Image 1 (cartoon, rainbow over the protein chains, first blue to last red):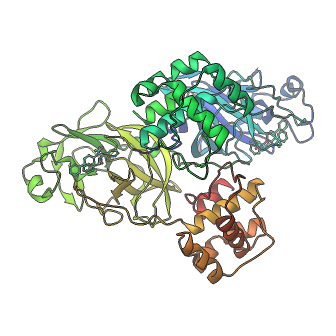
Image 2: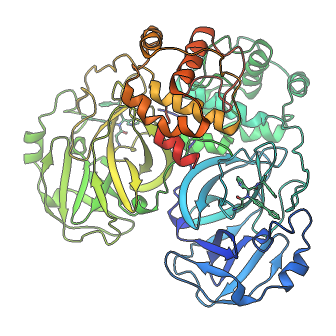
Image 3: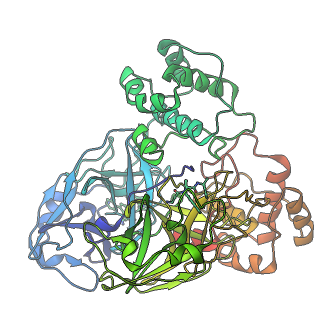
Amino acid sequence: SGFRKMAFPSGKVEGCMVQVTCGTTTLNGLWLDDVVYCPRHVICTSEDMLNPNYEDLLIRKSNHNFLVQAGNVQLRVIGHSMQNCVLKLKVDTANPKTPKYKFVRIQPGQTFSVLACYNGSPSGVYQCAMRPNFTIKGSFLNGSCGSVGFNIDYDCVSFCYMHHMELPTGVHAGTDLEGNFYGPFVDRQTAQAAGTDTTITVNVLAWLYAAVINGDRWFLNRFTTTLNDFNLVAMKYNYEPLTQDHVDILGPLSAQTGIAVLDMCASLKELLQNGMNGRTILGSALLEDEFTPFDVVRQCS
Amino acid sequence: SGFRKMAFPSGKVEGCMVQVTCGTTTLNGLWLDDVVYCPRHVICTSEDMLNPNYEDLLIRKSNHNFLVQAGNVQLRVIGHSMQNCVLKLKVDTANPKTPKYKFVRIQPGQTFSVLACYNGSPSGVYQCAMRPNFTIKGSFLNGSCGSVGFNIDYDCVSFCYMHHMELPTGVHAGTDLEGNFYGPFVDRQTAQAAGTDTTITVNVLAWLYAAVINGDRWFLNRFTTTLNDFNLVAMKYNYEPLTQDHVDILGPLSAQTGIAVLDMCASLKELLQNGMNGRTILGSALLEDEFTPFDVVRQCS
Ligand SMILES: *C(=N)CC(=O)N(c1ccc(-c2ccccc2)cc1)[C@@H](C(=O)N[C@@H](C)c1ccccc1)c1cccnc1
Ligand SMILES: *C(=N)CC(=O)N(c1ccc(-c2ccccc2)cc1)[C@@H](C(=O)N[C@@H](C)c1ccccc1)c1cccnc1
């Protein structure tokens, strides 16, 4: 029994985290094979932040200009380039601790583990969701940039996120490992705003299933409902519409609790309409949308 | 900016987690130097659970009876013993991945990282507190026993908890690495009950400081209060009395927010008396007592 925000083991990734330097600019990088990835805003100075031309700035630099530190060692830069918003710094040495990995672009609602790093030293691990507005409500301080988000599949690390920047709102934005930002965010010091942050309906449901399974089942109602019916109540409270796919994906949970999806939806409709009256689910006083169905299945089996 | 339940990197510990077997009983073990630690309830069978004599059961076993698996390898048992509630299984091979470590007995209110393991494979990492009743509200399934709790200090893993058993309440109990249980719990299948679970006053305060620092400062009040005054309101709501030590320990946070401890206490007195009205602090709809002052300092610098 028990349920908490659980991250993947961070060992396979710890050993890939190096330090990357330019004058008064240092941030973390990811060393895989004979390549070191980092955010390209490492080359900018507080003089050309409002609107950098990265092509032009990159030109002003050559292989020897970048200090690639792993532990107390140094690496030799041999070839550099710019893939969208990331630096690909080719090094003489391939990482001996390079796990089987893939780069994958995650979908809004999917969760991943973040290893927060300062100065190339892994500081801490925590679980995170790609919010529907393509932001993440993470815990990054100054120097956290280059920190990576990942899932572990069999023996294979799936890297999905590199952290670039905090938004005035205090939320966080960054790229896939091919250098594309999640959302419409740009790597410059201009007014960017996150859009309406909706709630991940299929996740909140996965939560309640988790709750039922642990023994919290007070909020279960005698009623039922329709997808259409329920979806018209979702929109009202700014919730992700629920699709049949979403219904299908919850099947495993349905089949373990002997509880139809729609009955659980009808309980959510109540909690949404009625509030929680000062009661609590899995020791939370509000509805939690940062666990996928898969997340809950793993922790509940 | 940002604040979440953050664990220590789990690499140094991942490589210490082995599998331990007896007939139809398998659980995780911790391999440090030429020793493998695990819960001694590994030798019991569902026939002698109500009241085992472990001395007598241990006698019935010899070095070759125990299957110590690390990855796809096997280890050779050379000397075995019983330290309070743990097995010390001497092996021919010392762990090549043995970090600098210490065994430390944690105090109620202190936090640590748990690496949850099934079948000797690290499954997941999450942050945990020693509750004042010496239980932990963790996430363990069947086979999780032998999973360890730790802090990392400089380069030194401090092991504080080995997990043994779930209590009817669904909370969790286990030992230090010298085999002593936290609390009055015993490794047998008898009625044991956790005592009154109080709230960790110094932690809730550390939280609010964290909140203020991120920008959530609505609950700040124009009032103040006295330790005595506040403590008489603590007891009412089942809270840890606040000591001058507790006041001292919060100093760093005081000094960064320019806010006197007692003023923060006076805000807590309000929230305790008044509730939260449907407002939220660091995206929580209730007061959070599972971060130490140190925890908050690290994440907030
Ligand atoms: C990463 N290690 C650097 C860092 O921590 N932050 C950051 C600084 C500068 C830039 C940047 C400079 C020039 C051109 C393009 C980007 C990006 C990130 C900051 C941070 O993001 N501050 C925000 C408000 C910001 C200022 C100016 C430009 C962009 C963004 C940071 C703080 C806390 C957590 N993560 C990052
Ligand atoms: C650990 N891998 C085994 C396990 O998962 N649990 C457990 C089983 C049996 C015993 C035990 C048997 C004989 C003598 C002494 C102890 C301890 C732990 C269970 C668990 O703790 N179930 C509880 C209800 C229990 C039953 C009987 C005796 C003690 C305890 C477990 C479930 C979920 C999470 N962690 C452990």
